[PDB]
Structure formats: C-alpha cells, structure tokens
Image (cartoon, rainbow, N blue to C red):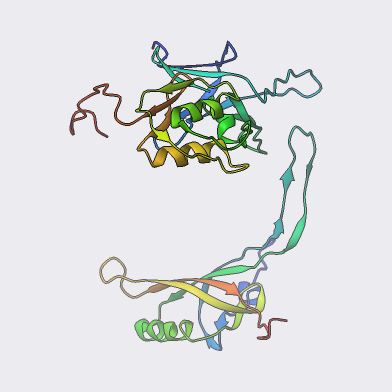
C-alpha cells in the first residue's frame, strides 16, 4: 500500500469453509461474459452479441506449519470431500457459496519436513429448484 | 514429374484441380468422378463465370485414357467464413441418361426377337454405342414394363442370362459373360501392398 501504514490483518478477511477455519496463502478469481462474436464474408464490418454471465471460479492455497500439521491437514481434507456445497469466506471477495472441485496435497520427508501445502480449486454454486422451472 | 493424371473438360485443360477421385465398378452400369477446383473473387471487380451444367469430361492417367464422362452433371459451390471458397464437380458415364430416363419404346411389347435386338432398340434412343460380345438368346415373349427405367430393364433381362452389364473406359456399354482376359500384375505382399 502507498505509505507504510498498511495493516494486512485489517484488510484481508480470515479464510474458512463450511465453518472450519484455515490459513490462506493466495487468492485468485475469474470473471467474464459470454460473447458470440461473428465476422461476415467479404465484408469490412463485424458483429457481436451477449449470451449471459460466465460462471466464476476461485483458487486458494493453504499452509500448515504448527506442530502436528498432519492431523489438521488430514482432518481438513475430510471437509473438502463432504457432500454438497457450503459457504466460503474468500479472503478478499467476502462470503460466497462455492463447491470444491479438486485439491492437491504436497508433502515430503527430506526435502521439506514440517510444512504441508494444499492447492484448491473452487467453483460458484447457487442452489436451484428441482422442478426445472 | 511427368503428370501421372490429366483431365480435360470440353478441350480446355484443368490446371487447378486441387483434388481428384475416380471410380470404375463392375457391379453397376456407370462409373463416376469428382474434382475440386479453387475459385477466386475480388470485390467490386469483374468475375467470369462458366457454370457449365453439361459438357464432356476426360481423364487420362499416366498418358492413358481412364474415363469418358457426359460431364458437369453436378455443380456445387462450397464456401466458408474461414478456410476458403472453392467449387466441386461430378460426372458419370455416357449412358447417364439411360440411368435416369424412362423408356420411350415405340410400342412396348416385342412379338418374337432376341435380347440383343431388344437392347439395341432401347439404348439407341439416346445414341449410346453398344459393345456386345456375349451369346445371343432367343426370347419368345418380351414386354417392357410401362414407364420403367432403362437401367432396371436391361439389368433385369441380363440377370437371367448371366450377362454382366458395365461400362468400358471409352464411352460404350459392354455386355460380357466373363473376364476380359487382360493379365495384370502379381500383387505380392511385402512388395507393393500397403
């Protein structure tokens, strides 16, 4: 931030998912709008149309350091695998309803012992009625 | 290399045949052909259009005749927003009209004749030269079905006498009871098979 009076704990929300806290380390997103661009033949003019909003996707990275990280790590994975979507407190985007889609757990015993990294790939998921309209 | 395939349409060579394909089938009554041609267009400038719906087409494979349409039986102009804009052509044997014309026989029922003398009076309404080499058969009664195609009746009558009905490479109609006897190559595995 401009000037040295930044307090990062005051601007970044604490991460969470389905109520279980965890320590976040990165925050990304993806937004857009579905187009239908078309270019005619032998013509010097093109066109465009709008076909609705595009589905968002969030990706986060979590770090575990404290003693007995395997238990907290091995216990948090049991939450990502739970059925159905749940509330996600994005560090910057605020609360948002998302559903997990993948997770890679990285670990080692000699190269790096005492820290566990886990990359995640979330997706927005808004509840819908079951009678198809 | 010396062009191993050349094509003519009415006597003006096709120098832009971006692809080709020829067929000759013994179990039918007419061959076929297909040629793809590149075509151009400049906006706000003149364009010369042929659009020949009918004319002769000839194909020579390695300095030898291999087909005799009559030609330009089909004309379609493909076109794309992307890749390109081209044209396609098609052709068939000289007897094409027999394959797609209902018979116009003088009366419609022979009294007493032979098969050869009947095929001559059916084909020769369209001036297609016959090439007969099979054995003649005597038929006390023949009566062509009213309005039936030329292809159907010749095929029907020649089936019961073991006559093959297929075209040659020159533009005739050849009726034979066996192989032409022209000995070919010894296609050996490991030598030329693919």
Q: Quadrant of residue A26?
A: bottom right
In front of the other: A115 or B18: B18
Q: Residue at x 66, y 35 (%)?
A: B79
Residue drawn where x is 80% and y is 38% of the image: A45
Residue A114 sits above or below residue B36 on the image: below
The N terminus of chain B - image quarter:
top left
Query: Residue B57's x, y, as percent?
Result: 55, 19
When the figure is inspected, residue B38 is found, relative to residue B26, above or below; the finding is above
Q: Residue at x 74, y 22 (%)?
A: B42
Percent x, y of residue B39: 64, 24
**Residue B95 seen:** no
Instruction: Name the residue nearer the viewer: A82 or A109.
Output: A82
Where is residue A49? Give x, y as percent.
Answer: 77, 54
User: Is B64 in front, or is B30?
Assistant: B30
Residue A131: x and y, percent? 68, 86
Question: How many marks can you see?
Answer: 0
Q: Is B41 placed left or right of A14 in the picture?
A: right
């Amino acid at each position: 931030m401009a000037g040295p009076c930044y307090n990062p704990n005051e601007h970044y929300l604490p991460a969470s998912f389905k109520g279980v806290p965890f320590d976040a380390d990165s925050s990304d997103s993806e937004h857009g709008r579905n187009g239908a661009e078309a270019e005619f033949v032998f013509g010097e003019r093109t066109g465009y149309a709008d076909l609705g909003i595009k589905i968002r996707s969030y990706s986060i990275r979590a770090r575990f350091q404290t003693n007995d990280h395997v238990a907290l790590s091995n216990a948090f994975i049991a939450v990502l695998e739970s059925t159905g979507p749940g509330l996600l407190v994005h560090p910057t985007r605020g609360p948002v309803m998302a559903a997990c889609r993948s997770a890679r757990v990285t670990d080692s015993k000699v190269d790096a012992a005492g820290v566990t990294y886990i990359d995640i790939d979330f997706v927005e998921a808004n509840d819908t009625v079951t009678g198809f309209g | 290399m010396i062009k191993p395939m050349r094509i003519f349409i009415g006597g003006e060579e096709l120098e832009t045949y971006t692809s080709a394909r020829l067929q000759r089938t013994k179990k039918q009554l007419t061959g076929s052909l297909t040629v793809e041609i590149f075509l151009n267009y400049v906006p706000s400038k003149p364009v010369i259009v042929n659009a020949v719906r009918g004319k002769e087409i000839l194909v020579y494979v390695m300095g030898e005749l291999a087909f005799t349409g009559e030609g330009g039986s089909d004309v379609t102009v493909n076109f794309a927003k992307g890749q390109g804009y081209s044209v396609t052509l098609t052709a068939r044997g000289r007897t094409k009209y027999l394959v797609d014309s209902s018979h116009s026989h003088p009366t419609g029922s022979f009294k007493d004749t032979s098969d050869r003398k009947v095929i001559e009076a059916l084909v020769k309404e369209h001036k297609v030269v016959l090439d007969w080499q099979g054995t003649e058969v005597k038929e006390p009664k023949i009566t062509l079905r009213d309005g039936n195609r030329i292809f159907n009746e010749i095929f029907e009558r020649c089936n019961q006498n073991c006559h093959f009905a297929y075209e040659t490479r020159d533009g005739k109609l050849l009726v034979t009871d066996g192989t032409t006897g022209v000995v070919g190559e010894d296609i050996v595995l490991g030598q030329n098979i693919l």
